[PDB]
Image (cartoon, coloured by chain):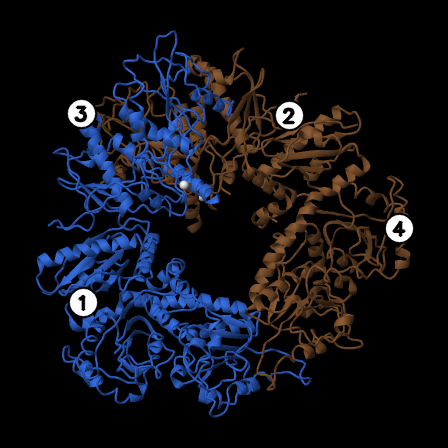
Chain colours: A blue, B brown
Amino acid sequence: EMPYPEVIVDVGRVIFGEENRKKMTNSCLKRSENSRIIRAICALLNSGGGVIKAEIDDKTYSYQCHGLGQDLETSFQKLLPSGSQKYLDYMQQGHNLLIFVKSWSPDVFSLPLRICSLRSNLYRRDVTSAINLSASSALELLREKGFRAQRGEEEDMRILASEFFKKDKLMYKEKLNFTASTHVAFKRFTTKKVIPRIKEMLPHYVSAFANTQGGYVLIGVDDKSKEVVGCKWEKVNPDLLKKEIENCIEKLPTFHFCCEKPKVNFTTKILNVYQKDVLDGYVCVIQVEPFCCVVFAEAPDSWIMKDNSVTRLTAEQWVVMMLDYPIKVHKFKEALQRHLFPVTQEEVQFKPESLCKKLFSDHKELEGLMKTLIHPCSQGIVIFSRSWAGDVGFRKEQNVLCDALLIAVNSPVVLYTILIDPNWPGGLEYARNTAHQLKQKLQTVGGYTGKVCIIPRLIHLSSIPLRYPRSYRLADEEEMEDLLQALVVVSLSSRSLLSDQMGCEFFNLLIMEQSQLLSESLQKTRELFIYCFPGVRKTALAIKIMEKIKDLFHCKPKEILYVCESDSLKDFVTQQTTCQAVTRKTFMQGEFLKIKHIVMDETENFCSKYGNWYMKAKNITHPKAKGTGSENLHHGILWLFLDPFQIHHADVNGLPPPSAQFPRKTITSGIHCALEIAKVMKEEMKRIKENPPSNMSPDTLALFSETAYEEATCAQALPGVCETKTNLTTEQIANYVARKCHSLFQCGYLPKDIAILCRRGEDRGRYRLALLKAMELIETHRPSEVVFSPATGVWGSHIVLDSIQQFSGLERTVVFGLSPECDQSEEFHKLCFASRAIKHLYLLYE
Amino acid sequence: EMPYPEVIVDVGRVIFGEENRKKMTNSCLKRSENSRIIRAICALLNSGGGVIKAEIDDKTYSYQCHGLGQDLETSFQKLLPSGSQKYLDYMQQGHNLLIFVKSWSPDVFSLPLRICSLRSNLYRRDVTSAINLSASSALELLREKGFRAQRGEEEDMRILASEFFKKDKLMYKEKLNFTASTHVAFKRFTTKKVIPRIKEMLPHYVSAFANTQGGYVLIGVDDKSKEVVGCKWEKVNPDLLKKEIENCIEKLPTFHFCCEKPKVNFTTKILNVYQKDVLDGYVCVIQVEPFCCVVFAEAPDSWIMKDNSVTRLTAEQWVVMMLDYPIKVHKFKEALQRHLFPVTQEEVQFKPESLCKKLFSDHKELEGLMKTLIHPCSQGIVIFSRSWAGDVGFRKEQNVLCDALLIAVNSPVVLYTILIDPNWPGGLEYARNTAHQLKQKLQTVGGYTGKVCIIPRLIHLSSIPLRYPRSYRLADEEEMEDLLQALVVVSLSSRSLLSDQMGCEFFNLLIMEQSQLLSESLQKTRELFIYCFPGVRKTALAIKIMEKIKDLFHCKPKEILYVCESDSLKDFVTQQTTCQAVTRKTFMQGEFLKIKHIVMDETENFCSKYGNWYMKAKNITHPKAKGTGSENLHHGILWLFLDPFQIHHADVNGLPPPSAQFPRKTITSGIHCALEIAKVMKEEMKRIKENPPSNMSPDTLALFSETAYEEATCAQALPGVCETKTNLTTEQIANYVARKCHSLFQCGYLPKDIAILCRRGEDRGRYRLALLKAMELIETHRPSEVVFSPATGVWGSHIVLDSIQQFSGLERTVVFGLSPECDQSEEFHKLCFASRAIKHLYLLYE
Ligand SMILES: [Zn+2]
Ligand SMILES: [Zn+2]
């Protein structure tokens, strides 16, 4: 029933036509419907953007033949002071009129107003006028009064109304010579019902002589030439003002920047007049001292919808909205977009590649007429996935198979839906929902200040369209640039597959900027000891420094050398760079006589049982061209990579007896894990600090400081998933662990992207038992086969069964777990797992 | 004749009264005088601030009895959108009314508008109205169009109106269905003289359909219900438009952000109507392509006075003003003010003490009845000096002795003048100058955004005042804080004694931040080699690091040592700190077996003839608690201070054979000289780079770069003086050198500040006299005596005669010179000047 994407606010029989905006003499219903339209439009404008539905006034109405009018567009012009041509679009459809709005996100070339208001309800005092304020003047007043509260003929006449204040006995009609200034107002009303006149006149003047200067308010004196006229003593009485002026000035909403909260200092007093024993009137005087903070007239005009209805705000709800991962994405966003989603003039591109290889594999007919279903066109990107609402965060539906999101130049963004079973009441509603929560992210998280719409459609490829006002489509290259950029920002903030496809390029773009700042220090020092945190990616950062070493030193690409421990991280470091990568059983064995420098990694793994490493490294390179036999004194480079918190080898290296002291650089600006994976490490690091083991020296914990993480973690980590499972012994896990991994690779994860990690690495061949064949006990659901190869478990496209000590350093996206309860005291294995997973961590602690 | 401080503008017989702002039916002269008032007032707002003179309307006028009015204050309200209660004050004086203004400097809590405009003369296209832009909307339009030029049922009516463009024939009165939208406007006129209506009307619509979107302009179509009425063919003709529409749209002042600079792309064509062979009118069509840059309608309303009269600006002169030492003064301003000019509740203080010790000394009656001359009061600061116009920069007079600049809380700032001779035409002309060139140095680059006034007075202490509207005086402690803070900035940008008194505290304020950013590196490294520039003040920075060493290491204040070369810089470092200061003939003689650290200075000067410095320095501390005999391995500090450009000893010191390579820190953020003194060093350093001598090694020149200065001298140097003299040999200079130095210490420079720096250090037996016996050849002007003591020439209050190698490291404010032509190849003595002077450099090269 009426498939639509966005927040409909049903209004009624309001009239967007010139004949009624010129003709209508019945002004009451006209102003009521005008106030309703302005309130609903500004409500959706300030809340989240969206679509406004309205009805039709005339039976042969059209937008072109009737125009818009004068009153409504003048109201819209006063509501929007910067520009109305970026947030207001119209259309008509049958017995329907359709208005569009957008999120009020101001650009960087204007004053920051977070929400717009009609009138800010904060009155000030000019020379003679009590004016209402716009958004900018209210913002500068709030900033000025906040900075003042955080810190701690013109002025003549001000002291002349003090004589009028302390008078108590006044002669009738006496035009005393004080006039209007920046400290006195003297506005009179002499009506019959004098109570609501107080609450419509002074909430203004009481704040006017509280946000500028001073204060004095009179009742009973005309405003032409400071004339007193008085009234008859039956019409005016000296009692009927004070009973309700107090009830007036108590309900004014008030905000306070301070904490020693005062109140408004009303000092009202009534004066009398006696001349010739015949009375002819009196004067009422109100004294208001200056206020330390802001005082509002009424409830502010910032209308924001709530609970699917229109709602009014309060003052304390107004000030906090009038005033005030997340940083580097917005910097590297353009280089991410120009590499992952390139926009050129070739044919259309099915951009998520790993899902299209599965959809072609299982459902041969589905990847056929799908190319014929969109349009014959060239400029475009198709993002093909499973449930996009569940990708951006929602419940997934069991019936839905796939959906597509199409971005093109002169074509709107659409969203098709593939459905297997004919669930027509249960499908289209879901097809509506993803066309809302995908836009309200791309205009909030992504920061796209542009007009875009996503149209829901259902295709049902197992065997009444809408309309949009021809400007919500894209225009040229630069708008599709911004839309793909905002989609990159949104996809790097949700738990999906496309997040894991973008985070690697984001990490590489960060590693380049970190290696630049290390190459800046390459100019100054020759030696450097680097103290790393758990999760630093020393291996990714130690590759980009070698090209800077070569480009700055002007030497050969063979004269730079790299030291590792095992063959596992010797692989994948043999590629991706140009150096002589060796193991610990090889750098202790290789006789490098044409060495020039040393840039090593994994410094915590050196055995003192056979030979030495530090003495050999300080006997190979530290005897460089020194001594009197060589005038050439070129100096070498010894960059070690110490991970001191994760020291687990009790044999002495030669670094602890000098405590590894040299020119230091603790790099707390390198961390690449998930936001919950880093939180598990944050929770686990402060257990060893409060309880060190029997082998670790507690002197190395002074270099670590708290609040280095959750600032570095807040600046350089990404969201993801982190699961847990309880009470699975190895007999109980024999059928439970197979089911949770069967549905994983259907979502787009390649079998290269996942890895089954196991605790007990000494039972490795036994761990080829009880899982691999158990994996076969879940391969009897889809006809296929799997191969597990722990020997060449680095570059195989198949799933790699690997251990924590067998698979060190190199990372992967999806990491599994299995843990029998080994010891009651040995709780160190949790320190291993989350040091290797990137985004998706599935862990089974038992 | 009318003693006044500021920029008076003779206006005339304008009326600031309510009776003529309500009564005057002759609207022509009324609106003309209103335009003159608004133009002159906004001219002095935008130009520099000042005062405005005016006459009187009524013979019994008073400001309180008549008020202000409505029209003028509404014009002032539209001119000032933020607030009028900070730039507009009034008074009346006899047959004269006076207005006051202030410089338009916006605060940090608002949008930066550098000059206020009435209307920016830049029209835009709304829904149906062609509005005029305010300053903020014009600013955001210019920023948006500049950022765009730097980079590279409502919309289809733009397509529907093209059949009205390429039609060329039409039938009469046909109500075609296009209306007013964001791409087509159709404003008509059917008058008799159609030329000047084009000149006044369409520049607006041409700026409307160039700064948003599209363009179309018609003539001859009614705006009520898209009606065509036409005119008779005698009244309208098809020729009398095109002859002058092109002359209209050519003179529009246009600014260009782009490079190709196109014109406005008019594509106009005239259209006709034939029906039944009965002509009844026609319609014209103007076509305007969207313009890449802004197009102004007329000359802008931003008025700025020039050549003592009112002047109008052009658009290219408008855009550059509507769009866009110097950074650290504004940060350390508060700490300078709270120490040099303290504001308390004690009695008045005569703050420059050196001139008050002189005026009492020579002219004891002057400091007598002067304390009674000001007022009996307590809260205030008196600033005596010499010619204050000369201190700001202006020609000094030959008779003036003193003038007082008095700051007080509830009293305005004033200025007196002490005069000897009865020269009354020559006095007041002086007194009116300095109360103009001081305030117009404070409200500009000093940065005072407040109201202040300085009153010229004359006293003529041998043995008709002005009036100000009681807000130009200060109010409380914060206004006096702000004025003293701005006067510190004003005094630290001119050539004065008070400048030389404030710079010595500004340097000590910057030394703390430099030492903090150096002591941040104490956690990281133990050894560090510091390469310094000529002028670094290593001696001032090598004192504040020792308190950080103590407070971070928690050791005794006698375990820190300091190495120097001579006894001269051993003095002044014996005091001012707590360490064991020694010389090169003492650190290579003393046996310091207690010490742990070494922080040395002046590393360039070591003699390798009899012994070694570096081998003993690396055999004392580098055998610290090392080896197997001590488990404790605490590590020391060896900070050397190398000035590599200024080495002149070619012996083997121990730094050249390893090229002094260690962990490096080349400090280009330490320089304390003058802005014109350091330019001599900049023009002298790049002579040695292009011509090194036979004893200097060119390998160390790679560390110094050009543009390592000009961001160091730009950020850490102060203004000053640098003079020269030519062809004064020692027979010619013997009577010439005495005259230029006798007039120096009378200006306010205390003794121990100035010092005579002679060049030839070997001929001191000649140099002790020839200048001393010349000195009392010029002390026959004022009866006094002189004492010269080069032996203890460091802390003596007498004037110090000193040499370049005899006086090194320590600085004096005023330096001198005497250089006979020694050799045609020896051009290094000019290098010895500018490393020792601070601000005042007097040089005599022969
Ligand atoms: Zn408060
Ligand atoms: Zn241009």
What residue is shown with label 2?
A: B4
Q: Nearer the viewer, mark 1 or mark 4?
A: 4
Q: Secondary structure at mark 1?
A: loop
Q: Residue at x 20, y 71 (%)?
A: A746
Q: Indicate the position of residue B386 as horizontal and vertical percent values.
A: 73, 37
Q: Identify the chain of the residue marked 3, using the numbered disc in the image.
A: A
Q: Residue at x 27, y 34 (%)?
A: B164
What residue is shown with label 3?
A: A26
Q: Nearer the viewer, residue B403 or A332?
A: B403
Q: Are marks 4 and 3 in contact (CB under 8 Å)?
A: no
What residue is shown with label 4?
A: B772
Q: Residue at x 60, y 46 (%)?
A: B338
Q: Where ligand 1 lies, by quadrant?
A: top left
What is the CA distance from the residue labelled 2 to the residue labelled 1?
90 Å
Badge 2 and badge 4 in a common chain: yes
What residue is shown with label 1?
A: A367
For disc 4, does the CB lie below 8 Å from ligand 1? no
Q: Secondary structure at mark 2?
A: loop
Q: Identify the chain of the residue marked 2, using the numbered disc in the image.
A: B
Q: Nearer the viewer, mark 2 or mark 1?
A: 2
Kind of residue indicated by mark 1: Glu
Q: Upstream in the sequence, badge 2 or badge 4?
A: 2
Can residue B160 be seen by looking at this rendering? yes
